[PDB]
Image (tube, rainbow, N blue to C red):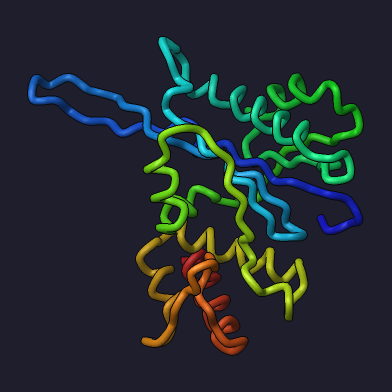
Amino acid sequence: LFSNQIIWFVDDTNVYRVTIHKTFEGNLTTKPINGAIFIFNPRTGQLFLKIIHTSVWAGQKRLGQLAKWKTAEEVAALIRSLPVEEQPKQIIVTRKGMLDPLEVHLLDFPNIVIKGSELQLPFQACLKVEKFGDLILKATEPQMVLFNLYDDWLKTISSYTAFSRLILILRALHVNNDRAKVILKPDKTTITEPHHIWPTLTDEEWIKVEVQLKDLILA
């Protein structure tokens, strides 16, 4: 994974989202709510969060399929906004339905390798982190927001270690949100700094939480 080339993971799982509701009359309303594309560099921790506002869906059917194409369009748009030296060499999609849309949208980038993955990388778990959930829910138009999902970790640990820690966090949040959040608050004094995503923990605290997160996923 960590060679000498820029790699992005692309997750489209959360682009088309709805809430469903049984009306007093007994019919089902399906109302789209804002979604997001997660585009993630595992070496640097850089996350490009493309917020997808509900206005993009129109007198449109099959929004689930259309969402894959909108994702591809947005990934290509991002690539075109970046200098060549910042463009990815490889794009790894978390769902196989993204392969063909991306192939078609990146024809002008013949050197980019597009591939699928069997990895469990639930960026959907970020929707359960207030910082992301609220930002997405409250958006009134599309926008892209940059985040550093590794906070200050890279000052003292490797990219490999940071990536593993992040995946454990996301997967644990995915499988049992309540228990994961307890695990990530090991002390009464535990805080998350305003510009950070994750709690400020000592090295010893991280060791224990990483084991506990892993155990939670196995359970």
Give the vertical position of 173 relative to 94 (above or below): below
Q: Residue furthest top?
A: 59
Observer-nearest residue: 159 or 208? 159
Q: Where residue 212 appears, x then y in whole percent? A: 50, 76
Q: Residue at x 40, y 58 (%)?
A: 130
Q: Where residue 23 appears, x then y in whole percent? A: 14, 25
Q: Residue at x 57, y 76 (%)?
A: 210
Give the vertical position of 207 relative to 28 (above or below): below
Left or right side of 103 for 143: left
Observer-nearest residue: 154 or 186? 154
Give residue 152's quadrant in the image. Answer: bottom right
Q: Where residue 219 appears, x then y in whole percent? A: 46, 66
Q: Where residue 192 appears, x then y in whole percent? A: 47, 74
Q: Residue at x 88, y 39 (%)?
A: 84
Give the vertical position of 4 relative to 115 (above or below): below
Observer-nearest residue: 168 or 61? 61
Q: How many marks?
A: 0
Q: Residue furthest left?
A: 24
Give the vertical position of 189 relative to 130 (above or below): below
User: The N terminus lies in which quarter of the figure?
Assistant: bottom right
Left or right side of 62 for 7: right
Give residue 71's quadrant in the image. Answer: top right
Give residue 204's quadrant in the image. Answer: bottom right
